[PDB]
Amino acid sequence: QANQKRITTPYMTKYERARVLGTRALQIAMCAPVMVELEGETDPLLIAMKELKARKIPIIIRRYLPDGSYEDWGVDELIITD
Amino acid sequence: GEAFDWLLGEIESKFNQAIAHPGEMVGALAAQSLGEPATQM
Image 1 (cartoon, rainbow over the protein chains, first blue to last red):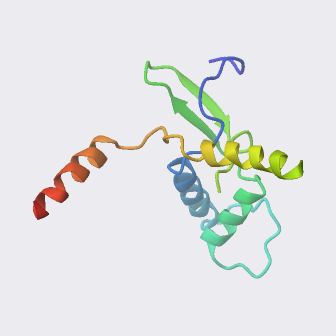
Image 2 (cartoon, rainbow over the protein chains, first blue to last red):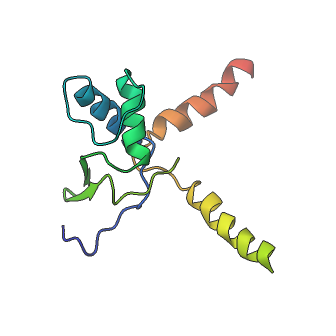
């Protein structure tokens, strides 16, 4: 759909933030570039959780509306619940 | 005056956190919540 007229919650559902911090931590865990300055972090889940609060994660979420269409929200445009 | 402006600030945030999350499996929730008491009835 167009960037106008998107109808979906701007907030990030707890299902999306569970699969974003999982998919991001799996990338970091394989030699993937890190967007944020890491300080004493050897653990990928803590790094990926840190990228999220800074809104640095490079993922766009594709939300399928139930009628077959879809919308593309980048992880910056969404509003982190917690 | 500032309490009221601060009060309307959280009535929004507290509400917008209640809204159901797209993707919840609801039938799993309503099937288990009606039948979980059943074991004690």
